[PDB]
Image (cartoon, rainbow, N blue to C red):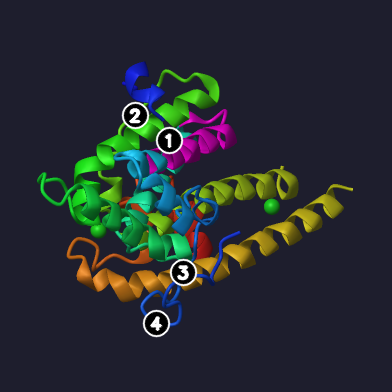
Amino acid sequence: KCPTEEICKDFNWLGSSVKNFSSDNKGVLVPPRRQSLCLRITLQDFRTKKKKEGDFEKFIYSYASSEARKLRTIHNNNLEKAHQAIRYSFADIGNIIRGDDMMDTPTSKETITYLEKVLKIYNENNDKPKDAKKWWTENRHHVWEAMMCGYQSAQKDNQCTGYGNIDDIPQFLRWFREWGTYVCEESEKNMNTLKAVCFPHENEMCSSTLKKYEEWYNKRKTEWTEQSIKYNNDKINYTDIKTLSPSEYLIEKCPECKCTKKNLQDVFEL
Ligand SMILES: [Cl-]
Ligand SMILES: [Cl-]
């Protein structure tokens, strides 16, 4: 159930631009949604928001709220896809605030330093958080509330949801799943279009369609290859996915995905 009005009144797939993209984060691709995430804290924002207690936090909540409003605007006729994008952005905001977001950008680098300086000036003696990880733990509920408020303002939706444990899932795994939610859907649809055209002049239709299908396949196959590198490199440290292939991970462990052996494994894993 959505936050009250009281609470609410107070508020493509890019291979480059990743920290350590040739090393630890080799193979990581940035979701378009992440590339576009609405959140930026400049020196000037810090300078002015720090003058009133709660204002720096409020500025962050406003960004989270606006990100969610934007996402619902984009996914206006699909509540599920809207809510999942919101969860993903929520989680990324979490990594940004905690200073371990993978994007190589100023906001990803500077947000934590700005936040923690504001926490130092106000929370030196009152037992409130002095570091960003503790802050996230105590305030993520507020962040989500702002997103739910923001989500509601798009089209007066009265249907909110929780975020489960999305912020506790390693960022690269979330981004891979998100890629999964787009591609397995494309894969299902493109298979059906192919079958309907080629196996229901209709010959020029089939060749044309088969051409476009191969192109879609090449693009995703390249992306599939890169992310598999990162997944296979990193799965060792997670006891509960270490024996899974990247196919099996998306098929079995991604409830938002709708990936199957037919639309994923047989298509990209040869
Ligand atoms: Cl197609
Ligand atoms: Cl995990």
Q: How far apart are labels 1 and 2 at the CA level?
A: 8 Å
Q: Are marks 4 and 2 in contact (CB under 8 Å)?
A: no
Q: Residues within 10 Å of mark 1 (few under 14, many from 20)?
A: many
Q: Who is closer to the viewer here, 207 or 79? A: 79
- For the residue labelled by badge 4, is the local secondary structure a helix, a strand or a loop? loop
Image position, residue 183 (x, y; %): 53, 53
Compare marks 1 and 2 and give the one earlier in the sequence.
1
Residue at left offset 42%, top offset 57%: 175
Relative to 197, say whether 102 is above or below. Answer: below
> In the figure, is residue 23 to the left or right of 184?
left
- Please give the residue where the numbered disc 2 appears in the rendered image: 161
The answer to which of marks 4 and 3 sits earlier in the sequence is 4
Q: Do residues under tags 1 and 2 come within 8 Å of each other at their CB atoms?
A: yes
Q: Nearer the viewer, mark 3 or mark 2?
A: 3
* Residue at mark 1: 83
Q: Which residue is mark 4?
A: 23
Asked if the residues shown at circle 3 and circle 2 are in contact, with their CB atoms under 8 angstroms apart, the answer is no
Q: Amino acid at mark 2?
A: Thr
Per the picture, the main secondary structure of the magenta-coloured stretch is helix
**Dot 4 and dot 3 residues touching (CB under 8 Å):** no
Badge 3 amino acid = Asp
